[PDB]
Image (cartoon, helix red, strand yellow):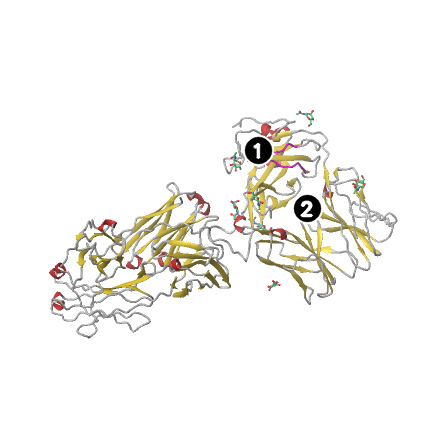
Amino acid sequence: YELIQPSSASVTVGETVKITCSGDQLPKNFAYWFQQKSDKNILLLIYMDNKRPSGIPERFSGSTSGTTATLTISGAQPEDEAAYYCLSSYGDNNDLVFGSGTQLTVLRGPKSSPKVTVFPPSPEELRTNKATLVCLVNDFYPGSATVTWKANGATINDGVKTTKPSKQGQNYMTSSYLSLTADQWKSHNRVSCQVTHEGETVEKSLSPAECL
Amino acid sequence: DSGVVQSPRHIIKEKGGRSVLTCIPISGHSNVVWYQQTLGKELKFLIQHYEKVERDKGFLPSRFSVQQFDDYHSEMNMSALELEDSAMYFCASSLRWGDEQYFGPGTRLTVLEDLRNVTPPKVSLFEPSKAEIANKQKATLVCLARGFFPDHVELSWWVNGKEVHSGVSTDPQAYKESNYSYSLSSRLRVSATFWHNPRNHFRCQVQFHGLSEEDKWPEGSPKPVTQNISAEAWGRADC
Amino acid sequence: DSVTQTEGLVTVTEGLPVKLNCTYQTTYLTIAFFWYVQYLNEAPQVLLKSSTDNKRTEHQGFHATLHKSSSSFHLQKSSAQLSDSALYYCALSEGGNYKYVFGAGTRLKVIAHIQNPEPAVYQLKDPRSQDSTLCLFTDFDSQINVPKTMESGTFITDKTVLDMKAMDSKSNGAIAWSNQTSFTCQDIFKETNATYPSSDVPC
Amino acid sequence: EVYLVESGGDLVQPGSSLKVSCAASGFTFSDFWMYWVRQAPGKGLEWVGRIKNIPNNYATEYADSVRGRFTISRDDSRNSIYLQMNRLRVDDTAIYYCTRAGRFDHFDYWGQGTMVTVSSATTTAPSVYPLAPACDSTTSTTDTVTLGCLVKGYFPEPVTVSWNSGALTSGVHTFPSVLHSGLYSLSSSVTVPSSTWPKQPITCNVAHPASSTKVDKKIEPR
Ligand SMILES: *[C@@H]1O[C@H](CO)[C@@H](O)[C@H](O)[C@H]1NC(C)=O
Ligand SMILES: *[C@@H]1O[C@H](CO)[C@@H](O)[C@H](O)[C@H]1NC(C)=O
Ligand SMILES: *[C@@H]1O[C@H](CO)[C@@H](O)[C@H](O)[C@H]1NC(C)=O
Ligand SMILES: *[C@@H]1O[C@H](CO)[C@@H](O)[C@H](O)[C@H]1NC(C)=O
Ligand SMILES: *[C@H]1O[C@H](CO)[C@@H](O)[C@H](O)[C@H]1NC(C)=O
Ligand SMILES: *[C@H]1O[C@H](CO)[C@@H](O)[C@H](O)[C@H]1NC(C)=O
Ligand SMILES: *[C@H]1O[C@H](CO)[C@@H](O)[C@H](O)[C@H]1NC(C)=O
């Protein structure tokens, strides 16, 4: 069948969170909780839906009632913000299955602001007659900031591509790109990259693209 | 029924586990009492009930709470099971106060630390000895069930599809081959003539008892469930 | 209150008599005394029960007469069959408390008597797995003390009687097995008073 | 010291066939069932199948997602299990992980994995282009300075991007890749104090395992 798991999750350092995995055949089959860090390493947190392996944090309990097993991170910590997948079986041949994984985020408190950094197309880049404008944004917490470019004060919606990664222990980042016809940038006027940091109507503007 | 009924007859569980025992008293009898036999056989009084759930208490652990029903069906609620609770829980019944009690088949439950330690046995049929046959004019078939844990087994001999007891001798109690490994052997003796008969079948069946419905078995190997493992051989080895 | 009875094992040889001692201690008027026999792998069943102070209460072999004076419901059986091998419980029911007192218990092990003892230890094989250090000690006297294991991987069970298809005498057994595939039945069976018959296979 | 090493991944055209293996070391491969598990980039963990040992008839079981095309095989003589994948589909592109299940150990050790790319495209060598500002956009808090490299034009598995061959580790920022017209792209930033680079070398060493991408790009000023 299918195993349900909340799409995400959020807990504040020190406090405690609860991830639920609902499985129709849970009552009949065991559960297993795994942890996947940005590093992509698979970590077995709990097994037999309530027996934690030595070497793992005691704050990782794993109860399980009826058709819903649960991982419980007591006094959640920072280095705990990663992916969580519940595992179990189904059918006569005990088929195996994972949940849709859960993305818990650990709130800290130090609300920082954006740190944009636009970058004009490379000379050799234009050589290939290509204008790829890289607009970055650093040191910010928490909410994702929608980095929208603008041309002469009018949003741009073509050839763009952005992300919303988060690494550097307590430090979020992004890499909002933007392609452009070499003869579009050479013939452009006000290449922008408006960032919108959470909590504030933020607009680090930094209206770039002006010099030569 | 004019006979006490007890269920289940075998319960294996892990600590913290929670099971329930059942007892169908002999029809007519009002007085129902639950007894527990521990290591070596020492009948101990738990809680007695007379005509509905009227009671005279005993050493019945608070975790265990039994009650009677209209049909007089009485069940024993076991909760927070511990290795110490590993016993033979018999249920006896009787009529008016003072005359002849009747024990049911009993429910032998075994609470263990690690279920994963449960495991079926390995039946092996060892044929007679050429010597024995010649000298004593007899054929002794040795059967040896090995490496299994909960000594919840019952070896049975089967010759030609029919069960047999004449000439059979199973070990009284299974030995502890290891700390987590038991073993039980038995033997059967038939004439050198019967053994020689190639049209004669011999089967040693070992009824093992494992987990059931509440099969919360680790998803890393086969759940050892109650089962029948055997080993069979025919007549004279062909020369 | 209590009903104390013999604590030994009372080993007996078929044919000789038996006698399990049982005395009681009650504060109320006893209503009836009973003897329970619980056979290996079986629930405890009544063997016989009594209420009068002299009724050679008889049943499938056993007999036991009660005597209030000296407070006793002793049990005895002249001839002892191997079937009698079981656990025995002495109990009673007394007035007032309604109590149904039970006796500690007494194990009973009747052994066989071999006419012409033919001590012998053979080594049987297993067509299945290649490993199989098995030995069979049979027809040895019912009084000899079968040796015990001296090392791991090895093991010597306890003697056991078998009476094949009602024809004649029975036979005492005791099998041993080990992993020390270096040993032999004679060695495995330390202190040996037997013949270890064996040789190469014809054909 | 229990070790599980996957091997065999590769980028191959759809409808193809790939046979990846899983190596073992640090235990009795004997009393353990092994399993296969892949995972799509942004997708969750997905179980492929399992293969019991000999005492269990080596019984094999596959998820529904690949019951008729994917197969597993065990080789005790080598202490390994394999995955024969046929009629592959792009949606098969993933990193395959193999784990184990014993009498008491369950899904404890996982291998690094092995990438399988099922797509109708070819290794498109990357192209790194220096990123540098200095357009004194009056409102300069240039307490520090940043820049990097724009690796663009690659598509195969992940790549590597160092700086000054490691020396520079603080102030670096390798963001997550980006799918653009079937071609990947990635940049790497670095932040130092205003007076540290125009003088000291701020080179970035890009790599692309797929195709010998021994690149170095001494970022000179404009
Ligand atoms: C048994 O008793 C426990 C008390 O801890 C209770 O939770 C449970 O519902 C009872 N179940 C039965 C079948 O008596
Ligand atoms: C279970 O049995 C195995 C083998 O007998 C033993 O190694 C282990 O210590 C036992 N208990 C547990 C929790 O593994
Ligand atoms: C197992 O053996 C250990 C010795 O290490 C002993 O302490 C323990 O009581 C034994 N447990 C069982 C269930 O036999
Ligand atoms: C196991 O025992 C049951 C009941 O005695 C019998 O019906 C069944 O055939 C046995 N199984 C085997 C494999 O002999
Ligand atoms: C009572 O006497 C008999 C006769 O020998 C003996 O076997 C029994 O052990 C005695 N009772 C006790 C408690 O020793
Ligand atoms: C053989 O004896 C036991 C069981 O066969 C086994 O555990 C042991 O390793 C072996 N003997 C020795 C001395 O190792
Ligand atoms: C040794 O002791 C026995 C007991 O069986 C006696 O019958 C006999 O004289 C002796 N037999 C052997 C083989 O030593």
- Which amino acid type corresponds to the residue marked 1 in the rendered image? Glu
Relative placement, left or right, of A10 versus D149 is right
| Circle 1 residues within 10 Å: few <14, some 14–19, many ≥20 | few
Magenta segment's dominant SS is loop
Any part of residue C148 in sight: yes
Does D89 sit above or below residue B207? below
Please tell me the numbered disc located at residue A116.
Answer: none
Q: Is residue D132 magenta?
A: no
Q: Quadrant of residue C196?
A: top right
Q: Is residue C151 magenta?
A: yes
Task: Say which element carries label 2.
Answer: loop
In the rendered image, residue C163, in percent from the top left (x then y), is placed at: 68, 38
In the rendered image, residue B173, in percent from the top left (x then y), is placed at: 64, 43
Please tell me the numbered disc located at residue B40.
Answer: 2
| Residues drawn in magenta | C146-161
Instruction: From the image, tell me which residue sits under label 1.
Output: C151
* Ligand 3 visible in quadrant: top right
Q: Chain of mark 1?
A: C
- Which amino acid type corresponds to the residue marked 2 in the rendered image? Gly
Cβ of mark 1 under 8 Å from ligand 6: the answer is: yes
The furthest residue to the bottom: A154
